Image 1: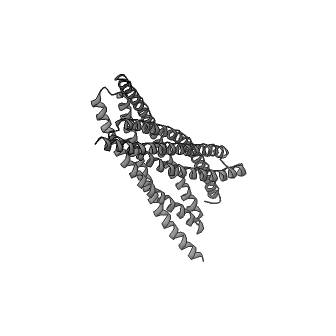
Image 2: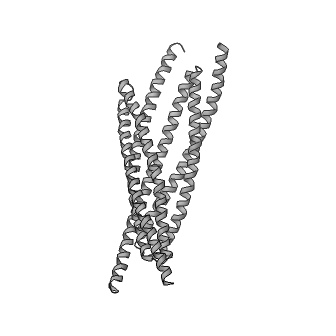
Image 3: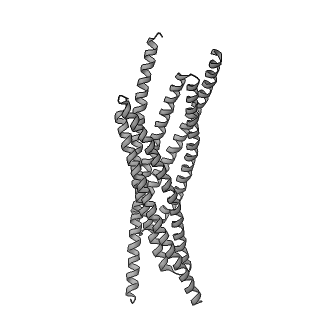
Length: 173
Length: 173
């Protein structure tokens, strides 16, 4: 049936159109969310570096103020991470919708509109993978800073503790 | 009551002992799992590099065999990732147990055993953070390889598609 297949092609082109738009929308929203998250990681990173540069103790005021800000910054980082996870889920659904739309286009003979859709899905994936990689690069810098901070803190801890133990040893031991 | 506090100290020292051991055990198991995961990411990384070096098509046999192996390698990577997530959860509980054990030790006056426990928890955390960072470093290499592969594939896709469109244009358009 010539007219039946024409109708199936038309119906699928309506699905492709609506799904492509939803994918574009969710893609940009997701990229925006990851970028907001990445900024928050960079912010938290410099704070750890500041705290570490003050370690040993000495300036007990700055040290505690910086640590207080870190607590709040961890919080902001966490909310922005959950926000992007939420959009990531929606984005995956959007990707599935488009892929199934491309498959449907294929099954009904709209091979053209199928390849086209398949290619746009690809570019959207590459795009998301790249902003994701930038975020991961930021996470690596944050982790290194957290590690250095723990390195220093545990070190200062051991030294202050060896001291107290040595002083306790001299108090008759 | 001198004897009451002695008993509370003894009871807490039993908790500290058992919790420290559980933490050490889960820590090593978790580190082992992350390392197994990291190896799997490195393996998948070189496979992507091989596939990308074959791109454009030409050797359609090697290309598809390599892609077939990748499918299986993604699977192995995924199972080892879920395995480490499972141990990560158990590990977090172990960390919570030890921290609460340190708090209890403090509340009952076992200040010594408290600081001690607090310091071991710290080192265990630093340790886990470092193997985690190695894994993240591997993930970064894998992501870059996946990105390059997508870069190339989308490029070859566009070129083969422009060709088919141009050839279709000449078939009278």
